[PDB]
Length: 56
Length: 62
Image: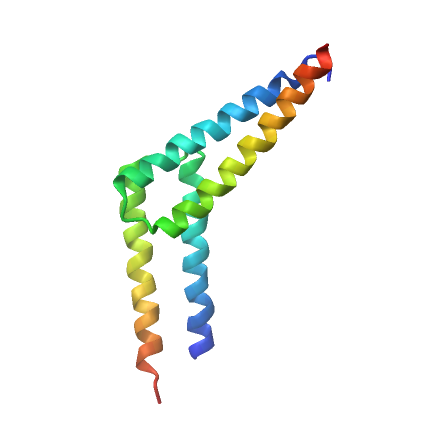
């Protein structure tokens, strides 16, 4: 279902914002952040692709 | 508050540390400036508040 994909999407966004908060508070090192950001970015792309898929 | 508000100065140093951490992101770039700028404004806002709080108390000494 589309909307099921839609809220899984904004969860990834929430993860992105939360991750930003964590680093700023000195919880993570720069190098790790990039990788974890890419991992989230990748999953967002997957979710987005699903939305582009169901055009029917 | 009975010299316990020296913690306020400590609370300031935290935001300053945050500022430096955020600047690391700016330097590396590739994180949307709009996203970084929003955080930058939030920190700058916190600094100014705490800064104003400090001078008020230091004034209240005499």
